[PDB]
Image (cartoon, coloured by chain):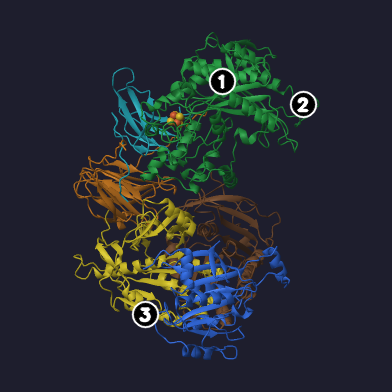
Chain colours: A orange, B cyan, C yellow, D blue, E green, F brown
Amino acid sequence: MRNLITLNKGKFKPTASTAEGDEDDLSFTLLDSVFDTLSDSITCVLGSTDIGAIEVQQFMKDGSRNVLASFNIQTFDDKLLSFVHFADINQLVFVFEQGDIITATYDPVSLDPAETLIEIMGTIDNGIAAAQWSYDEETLAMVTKDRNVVVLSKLFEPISEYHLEVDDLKISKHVT
Amino acid sequence: EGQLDSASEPVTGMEHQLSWKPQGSLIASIQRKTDLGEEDSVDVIFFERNGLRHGEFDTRLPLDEKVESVCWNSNSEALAVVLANRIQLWTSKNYH
Amino acid sequence: GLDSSHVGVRPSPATSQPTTSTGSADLDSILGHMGLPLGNSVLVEEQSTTEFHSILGKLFAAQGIVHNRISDSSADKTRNGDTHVIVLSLNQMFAKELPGIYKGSRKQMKNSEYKDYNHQFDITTRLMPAPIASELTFIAPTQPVSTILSQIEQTIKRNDKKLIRIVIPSLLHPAMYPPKMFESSEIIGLMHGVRSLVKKYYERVVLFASISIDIITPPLLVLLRNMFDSVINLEPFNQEMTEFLERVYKSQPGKIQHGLVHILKLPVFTDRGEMRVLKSEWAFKNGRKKFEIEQW
Amino acid sequence: ASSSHNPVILLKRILSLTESSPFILCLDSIAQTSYKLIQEFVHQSKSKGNEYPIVYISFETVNKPSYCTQFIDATQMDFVHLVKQIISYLPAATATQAKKHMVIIDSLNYISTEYITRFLSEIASPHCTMVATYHKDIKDENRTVIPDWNNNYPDKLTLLQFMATTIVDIDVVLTGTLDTEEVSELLNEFRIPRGLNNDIFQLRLVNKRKSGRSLEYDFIVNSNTHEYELL
Amino acid sequence: SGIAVVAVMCKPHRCPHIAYTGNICVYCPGGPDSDFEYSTQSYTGYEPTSMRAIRARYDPYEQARGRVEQLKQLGHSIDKVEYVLMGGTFMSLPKEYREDFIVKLHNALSGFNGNDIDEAILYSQQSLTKCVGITIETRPDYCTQTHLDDMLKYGCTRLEIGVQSLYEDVARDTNRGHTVRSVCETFAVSKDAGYKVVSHMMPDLPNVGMERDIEQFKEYFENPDFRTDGLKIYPTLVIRGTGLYELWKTGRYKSYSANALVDLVARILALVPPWTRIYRVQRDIPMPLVTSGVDNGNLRELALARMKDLGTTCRDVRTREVGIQEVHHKVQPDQVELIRRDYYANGGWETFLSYEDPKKDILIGLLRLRKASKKYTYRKEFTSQRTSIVRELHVYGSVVPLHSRDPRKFQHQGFGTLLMEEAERIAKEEHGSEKISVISGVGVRNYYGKLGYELDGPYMSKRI
Amino acid sequence: QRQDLVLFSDQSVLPAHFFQDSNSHNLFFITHQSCTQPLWMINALVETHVLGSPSSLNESSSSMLPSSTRSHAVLASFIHEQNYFTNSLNKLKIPSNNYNVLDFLSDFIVNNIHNKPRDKILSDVLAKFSAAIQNNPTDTIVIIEQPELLLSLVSGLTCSELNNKFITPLLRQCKVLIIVSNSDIFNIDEYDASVHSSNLQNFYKSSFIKSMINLNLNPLKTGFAKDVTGSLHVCRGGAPIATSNTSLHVVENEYLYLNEKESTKLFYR
Ligand code: SF4
């Protein structure tokens, strides 16, 4: 007998950061925006893939724009699949389609991204079909285009690997 | 640890819509039935963890849609169906 | 930091932590980590006069020696694995009691890179042969605690590279331990200092011990049980249940068991506030190959 | 080789001393003492055609029995000399399983627990075959456990039960019209109804075998015709 | 007083659903093909009723008469008895056997010595030692309309159709010949006829986990299809002669421990809707022949201790009953109120009325009412206009003492009239019905004929 | 489902004015069954004293680093070591610099307590805190963890001497004291500690007499379930409240709590 009603409808536009005074966009499209863990923050990431530049910045509850990293990758056409931040050790995890997992490092007191380091931890060849994190940010499962699924730990160590096969079929009909 | 447990039961028209009910009961997927008669429609199908079919309910949409993703609420109340223009919310009481 | 050698270790599936393996079949499975985390000790207990647990007291230690002896020009990776096992007993028969390897297979798949994992064991086969004093040492327990506490620290400090595995065979056996050490202060302070030393070198040190509870007053058991971080109890069947099983089991010699298993405490799982006690669910069996723990 | 013994035949086998251990424990009370038990030992031991030389240790016995060959009285002399004198009539050799020097003890209540093991560690030689007796009802002296927060040492009964290879205990069957509840009531009043110290007693036996397991055995024993039957 | 239950037995036979599956269902013990071979299925023949049936060579007359006389001689005097049938599928047998069986069962009490079942029931209506219904056990495949007409003519009042599961692999792997979904239409057709329907469940089965066991019961109680008026829970016990023991012999089967089962029962009892009577979690079993499982004599005796440690104790009818007279009248009760619940079940709206104490949750009297639908009714009585049916009247309110000024020397003899007029009020106003009917056993066709209801076919009806 | 955690009449767990009142003392007594550990409550107490709210149960824990706060916190324990305290409590993110952490396990046993006169040991173990709290005198909270174990360490010590040499001076010098311990001695099946083991139980009873509030974390009854871990009890201790306001008292309620991945949930039956 209950009904559903709408309370609020909020919106805004993530403003790309450039040195220019007018500071308009550079065709930067947002790839991912997340719900930060109840810390009155919304971490968004935008970029231009053709030239190969990405930018991650936090939108505060009041509306203060703060940038922690803005870096350009040498390659291009590299679409994202999952970006997260631990918010306890203060790192950043990016998953790319080519095979590179990007680990970014930032400081809280450094308002500018001048001290954000990058790590290009081990690549997965032949691209990656998809990847996903768990709810607790502990298990990293992903699948390669060659029907091989690999599960990695939270510290980028291999939990296991397994070759998915069409010949594997746990049928629901055995005649015993 | 990366072992195998079970493989699904083959069904016709199963698209790439995959999502798990947080309570831990039913997998949600989208099916299109274009066979003869008036049964043809667009349905949502639930799959048990043993890869066995269970339960179904049809959306009243026209047979020409294209649904992107299906989202389970953080709890077991709201099901979000995502389209190009409209976004729909479904909930069940008394299995209806 | 400083140099360190881990004789064999894999990431913990449960919490992504360095984890060793006792070499057991299902005991390592029921430890929650698919193994023993680096730093948390364990305890196993037996109800009656039997000596099932003694078998386990060998396996662990033997495993370490294997994990050290199959690296010298026998492992192509030549990976840095070194152990210096310390035994605290008044009888040295263990020096010629390690069981033999079955076929190896230290694979883990289903500072260096550590892929080593459990081997395959069998109880009838003796080891070939046995480590020298440079690999493994014996310390009599009857000496005063000051000398022992100084010497353990000296041994670990002078061998910084090596991984540390310590085994206490049948602690508090009246045939070797005099009443002058059953006094409350002595053993509790000894283990308090041992825990201090073990957790001080939290990176690689692991300790193992077992006692008999049928002849120990409950207060001392309660005092002791808070010193460790894991408790497993093995209770053998009564005679009547054994006769009932043998009368019923007529087609299986291997289905015969000896008793059940109780879980009182687990590794780090419990320190985060987890109720992990679980009793009267498992069943144990000593076997020709290894030690089996199944469901009953 | 004989194995899987008939329980009555097995009872004889221990009683005939076909098997042997360096320590045997027997228990008695003020309701049934163990003189007839030693009678059964010698009756079913020397009937095999064996002498079984016997050394006697007495703390409660007053006169030299017929069972023993040699003699030593330990009431006047103490531990530091008994550790000497025990070896004088006991060679240090092997083979408990056969005709050797059997060391028998009538009472074990009068030795401090702090030196029970130090004693027993120096007696149970592979030639030596030890049998001892303990009085269950007599309360242990208060100065053997030191009931303070320091001494976690166990009592005397459990120490003996854990150490002895085989355990035998006896009790007297009351042929009268009474009940053991009334017997206990009168004994707590230190009263003796007629019917104690009989000759047809009941026995309880436990042997540690097969790497540590144990099986409890009960029977009915007649000590005049030497009849062992099941109960 | 003097409510009596006298169980009878039918001759051995074979349920035909074996024919298209090969053997009996796996859990069914014994049977004609088994070593016993003088015994109906699901009974080993070692029950006291089995002994009394064998010595009579499976004859209803002798069994009924002997049990009635024994009960009378023990010290209780009987004037209200309800028959229950057991064994296999009674409806499978030929035509004449069922007719003769029923006629004998009615003439045993009526004292009549005739035939032509119509006359037998007509004489049984006007007889002492009144009969308050029959309980026939039958399968989904045999509940078609012709058989339902047969049961209505016989005098049956409530059925018990087992389902044993809601999953679909269990039906084929247990060699039971019906899809799960058909039981829903069986319930739908049965309920519109006024038949109280009860089911069965078995928690542990092969290839079933504790989870699936939990949410199958949850779906049974929540889904508007599996809402029925009763339940029976049979924990799985393995008899040596069953097809279940073969699985354990081949190692293809294992059971639950004690803790798991007691936790499952504790969870299950904390979900029962307040209009269903949990019959027996502590069922009756052949004890010594079981090889696998756990003791079931005092499951609820520990489950109650569990709910006292977790909260939300049981709410079924049985635990809240006070009885006809002085069962718990050692203390004067509290505030008495009328509670009315409504629910949708099997394509129709149904109402449950009760007189309860809300502070301590006891039960005194209850009534069930159903508004007839249009997609399931077929009787010529119910296909002429809108109508409503009183599926069950139940008055434990024959209690002499009470709270809130009980009648002094009238002692709640008009208590049932309150509920009857309450039902008629909403029949006239809410349902908008033009005829109201009540179903009852033939022996009690007069306690309803005084309020104005008149007889048509097997029904007691009056217009508006 | 979830319910708030309130422990006083002012609808506040730790009143601020308690620290604002001079010439006063208070004592809390916490007992946990040793099958579970109360760390998830020590964390909440520290956060609510420093940050002013329960920062793990009722409030989020994303900025949990109370280091260099205007308030202070001092924790000391025997069961664990300095290495564990630093590594873990910093992995639990319990502050460091506006904070004091005290070990008495690592290297303390080895001839630093053993074979020395008892009076010197007691005097020095008291002087450790008597000197470590001189810096910030009136904005600290101090918690000791399972101190009765020390009784079994000192050669032949009874409850009275340890109490009057360690506990009461600590509460007289400091504003408020919190003592946490375990109660397995009262839970030995078919054995009576009242026979000859009453020395340790005397300490528990004395502490409960001296305490002001009593917090109990106890395991579930006969079995073990999944959705619930244990039971939480709040009770009024022996001593009265030494406050200066009159309307103050203690609320009286029982909770059921579940713990999983450092996340705790409280609710009602
Ligand atoms: S349907 Fe009934 S009688 Fe037939 S096999 Fe199954 S349980 Fe037995």
State how far apart marks 3 and 1 are (Cα).
90 Å
Residue F24, can we see it?
A: no
Task: Residue under label 3, please give it.
Answer: C154
Residue B75: percent from left, percent from top: 45, 39
Is E49 placed left or right of A164 in the picture?
right
* Disc 1: CA contacts within 10 A as few (<14), some (14-19) or many (>=20): many
Q: Using the image as rendered, state which of residue D76 and residue E316 is in the foreground.
A: D76
Label 1 beta carbon less than 8 Å to ligand 1: no
Task: Judge if badges 1 and 2 mark residues of a common chain.
Answer: yes
Label 1's element?
A: loop
Residue on which disc 2 sits: E411
Asked if labels 3 and 2 share a chain, the reply is no
Let me know if residue F143 appears in the view.
yes
Q: Amino acid at mark 2?
A: Gln
F105 on left or right of B66: right
Distance (Cα) linking label 3 and label 2: 93 Å
Numbered badge on residue E156 = 1
Residue type of the residue flagged with mark 3: Gln
Q: Earlier in the sequence, mark 1 or mark 2?
A: 1
Task: Say which element carries label 2.
Answer: loop
- Quadrant of the displayed image that contains ligand 1: top left
Whether residue C195 is situated above or below residue E365 in the rendered picture:
below
Asked if both marks, 3 and 1, belong to the same chain, the answer given is no
The picture places residue E36, in percent across and down from the top left corner, at 46, 35
Residues D108 and C99: in front is D108
Q: Nearer the viewer, residue C49 or C96?
A: C49
